[PDB]
Image (tube, rainbow, N blue to C red):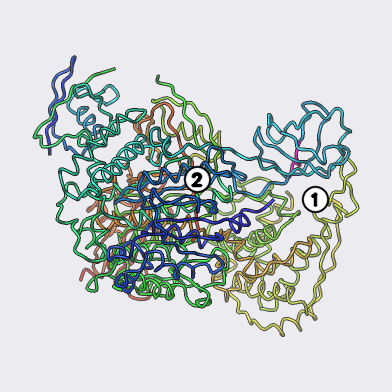
Amino acid sequence: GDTAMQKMAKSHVFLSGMGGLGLEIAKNLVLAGIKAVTIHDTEKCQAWDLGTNFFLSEDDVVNKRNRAEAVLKHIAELNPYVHVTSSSVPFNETTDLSFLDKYQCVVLTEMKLPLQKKINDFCRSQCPPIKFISADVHGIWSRLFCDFGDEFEVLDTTGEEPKEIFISNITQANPGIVTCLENHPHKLETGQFLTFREINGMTGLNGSIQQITVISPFSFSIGDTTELEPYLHGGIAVQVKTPKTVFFESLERQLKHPKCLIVDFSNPEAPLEIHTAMLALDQFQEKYSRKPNVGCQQDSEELLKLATSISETLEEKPDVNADIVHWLSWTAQGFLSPLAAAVGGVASQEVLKAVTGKFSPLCQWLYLEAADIVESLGKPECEEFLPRGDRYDALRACIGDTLCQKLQNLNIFLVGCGAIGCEMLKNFALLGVGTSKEKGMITVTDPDLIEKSNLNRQFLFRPHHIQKPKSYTAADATLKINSQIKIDAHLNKVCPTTETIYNDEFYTKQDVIITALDNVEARRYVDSRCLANLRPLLDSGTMGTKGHTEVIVPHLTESYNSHRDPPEEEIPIATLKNFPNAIEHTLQWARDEFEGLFKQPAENVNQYLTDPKFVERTLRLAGTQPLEVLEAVQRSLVLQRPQTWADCVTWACHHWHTQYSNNIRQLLHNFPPDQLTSSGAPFWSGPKRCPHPLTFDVNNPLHLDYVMAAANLFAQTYGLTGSQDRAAVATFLQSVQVPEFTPKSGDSRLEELKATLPSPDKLPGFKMYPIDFEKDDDSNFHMDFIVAASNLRAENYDIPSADRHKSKLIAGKIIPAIATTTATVSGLVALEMIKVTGGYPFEAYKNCFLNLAIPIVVFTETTEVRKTKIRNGISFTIWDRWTVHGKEDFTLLDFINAVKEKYGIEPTMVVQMLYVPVMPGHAKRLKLTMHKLVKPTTEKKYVDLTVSFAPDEDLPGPPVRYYFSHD
Amino acid sequence: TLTVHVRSEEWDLMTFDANPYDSVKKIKEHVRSKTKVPVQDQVLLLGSKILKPRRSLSSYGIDKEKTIHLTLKVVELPLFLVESGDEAKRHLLQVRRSSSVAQVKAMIETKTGIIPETQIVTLNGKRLEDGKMMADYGIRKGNLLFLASYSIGG
């Protein structure tokens, strides 16, 4: 066969009409790697086009160049491996359509419906059929159409690589049960097809394709195996990809009976109503050779008449929606660049689906809208939406000058200059965000640099930019889109260390915050920061075809931290411990080890010293494994406690020998390499790999790298210093001697452990310091440990090594961004951003989870605020924070009383543990003065503390901020 | 602002404040406070035209009227719903209008193996949330419930 990428490399595309929409499509397609993209337009540039088109320039409008031919050079630069060809050939009923035969797909924008029909008829007639996609954006309303032909074959629906399964046994019968390895389960559907290869016994099944039915989980019936010989061992099955045929109808047939996907199920009949209106607009242009003028009652009425007439011609009758028609007549002359970017992304992906068959296509129509952006304006004045001659006239005709002015003065904080961030900046510039010199300021920050990429290459970044900061480069590139835009580019990462740089003042000055991140931790840190300063947050994510948008407004919605996360799929326990097959296994095992060595032991010991009841809690927990925790504590306390960095180094050398030689050798003693399983098949077969233990070498850098990282980290856990001297560790390692290994064939002690364990009083001022993992900071050694630990484990199981950069990406499970999804997500996030700057109600804001592979777009209203109340108290949102002003001389009792006196609820305890009733000397803690009780050590004006009220158990409360001085 | 009048064969005339932009559902909620209570009974009509609940008064061409009037009328508790998976994996579940939201999430847990506490579903474009009833959300036969997983990248 030929791959989806190979198919794009052989395929040519024809795009007509180069407004904002035609460009957005061309951009994404050329970045994707289409062999040839033939741009075509007939009109010459105009000052209005500067608002919609991000490559056009003031110079081009004066010279009256053809829209396409002015932007061809800037588009071709995007992807130099693609042949972009311009065309000015006039398009009429006269013009022959024979020149379109060469193109595999044809995309039409800004074209009459009659001419579009004629082309559609020609495209679907040809053999093989030429695929047809029509997209237009008039005002805040859009239309998208797909007609790939009467029959279209989708070669790959899931878009995933075919699965491989390992067979434990096949019964000889008709329905002969086939059961997979107990270790390796299969997720198969009752209709799927498998091809079996390298089976023992049933030699006939090696070249056969059988349908399988899963009547019982983890088993299936392939067919009649009674004739065939009996199965012994082995048997790998490969999923067979089966094409899915979807049928299409011509444009003329679909207008009369449209088949639209529903974006928002709240308004299920909304797409058909839009179809009626959009089709009326086309008739209005045909009858009067112009678009409806804004605020003209005659035009708005005539359109409603047409829409009323069309509603009769439609199959299901629908009832016309007057609100939609009215808004269409007003905005018909305008162009909303973010909606265009969103429609552009989707439309683009459909083209790829047509030349590749990589996903199931759109079924005919898709109507997207920004009605939520205008509905909240009520019934506004028509004078607002009149053109003033500037570049933003197109936007003004959609949202009115009032909201345009709010955007111009905005102060946005863009966290992350990745693919989403770069698109966001282009969407900002067309919208005119932060273009007013007096007030507006966009602040964008990203700490990373640019990479060669070559594939999945970004449109702002170019080759000569390689190894130059992302944010700086984008900012400089963005100004070329809109000169008036004001951007403050920074290289600082948004994390606790920079909280001084991005202080509470900064967040309060910023009117909106937008996140373009790839890790959840940073999302939570930004969400928390925005909650304290009571500012909104706009999050987005891209995972291949899938994307998501979450809008968080102050006091109207919940936060990102509230929204909880499901556990990711777990690599089978035991497969990670003893049978790794891939670098993904060793990398994950190292992270499992890191927490099991440098974090969890330290917390267990610190918990033993702090809690006198720790001993009871652990006895109660998980019988038969309290012994394991207890012995692990006594080991860290006594046996393995290092008093010197050399003791840390010896512990690293002894640990390296146990994980990569002794533990291996005992597994081999249990499961020797010659050993065979039931059915006389080798045990180290297929997914299982025979390891070979390693021998420590000072000269080998992997061996040294492990010791050097482990010891410096081990020292941190106990508070010791580290030296970081390789030669010193090397020479010393020769001197140390390691205990010999002996493999093994295979509660009175638990009482002994209770006695042996040193009582906490006996160990004074001893504390251990858990380490939390941070990939970013390479001077930590945190990542250095992981890379070594994985690559060394790979050596043992004959798995290929993993570089630093490769391993980092594998650990992040980061997916390369795709231009279709990012452009879509970024347009939607931009649209919501308009609603926020307007201060719109909760109802207007709508989140969105989309997947272009299906395709399905889901619009949902945002999650409402959830107020939490304690018995006989007032309810408090997440956004609320309680503030207490004190005197310089105060007590915790005088505070607790003051809490009940203001709000009507009194705290049982207070955390920063500062005071518990159960704690001994609770009357001492309650008499303590406030400056002695809490020591900021910076004589801070205020201190933030937690509060809890118990009606059974204690229940949290909203954060409390106390001011030492009333002032 | 507006005043809306409701004529009923077996019930008293109802007059209350209203807004043209507000939905017919909002009018039915306004009716509930003044008389009869709940909207499930209500099936509003004007002349010969049926009035859909989601559509606004302005969607039916109401304009330049200080006050408007409508003729209210009264007309399968267990229904079939199909629950869409994270990756093109539909399921069949039976629900009733009088079902607690947690009960329905528990059905998803058996079907998908996803704990109901952390389940994320969207029904008729409204996030499916705890402490609610299916009737409150508004459910009709043939509706679809969508399961979603959050995406990270870019």
Is A206 positioned to the left or the right of A957 in the image?
Answer: right
Q: Residue at x 35, y 69 (%)?
A: A65
Q: Position of residue A121 (x, y in %)?
A: 46, 41
Quadrant assignment for the C terminus of chain A: bottom left
Q: Nearer the viewer, residue A766 or A59?
A: A59
To which quarter of the image does residue A496 belong?
bottom left
Q: Is residue A121 magenta?
A: no
Q: Is residue A715 above or below residue A951?
A: below
Is A388 positioned to the left or the right of A654 in the image?
Answer: left
Q: Is residue A887 above or below residue A232?
A: below
- The boundaries of the magenta stretch are A179-183
Amino acid under disc 1: Gly
Which of the two labelled residues, at mark 2 and mark 1, occupies the earlier sequence position? 2
- Disc 2, SS: helix
Please tell me the numbered disc located at residue A123. 2
Local crowd at mark 1 within 10 Å, few (<14), some, or many (≥20)?
few
Q: Which residue is mark 1?
A: A686
Q: Nearer the viewer, residue A334 or A928?
A: A334
**Furthest-left residue in this view:** B66
Please tell me the numbered disc located at residue A217. none
Is A476 positioned to the left or the right of A9 in the image?
Answer: left
Amino acid under disc 2: Cys
**Furthest-top residue in this view:** B10
- Name the front one of labels 2 and 1: 2
To which quarter of the image does residue A825 belong?
bottom left
User: Circle 1 marks a residue in which chain?
Assistant: A
Alpha-carbon span between mark 2 and mark 1? 50 Å
Q: Is residue A201 above or below residue A691?
A: above
Whether residue A175 is visible to the viewer of this picture, yes or no, is: yes
Q: Nearer the viewer, residue A767 or A129?
A: A129
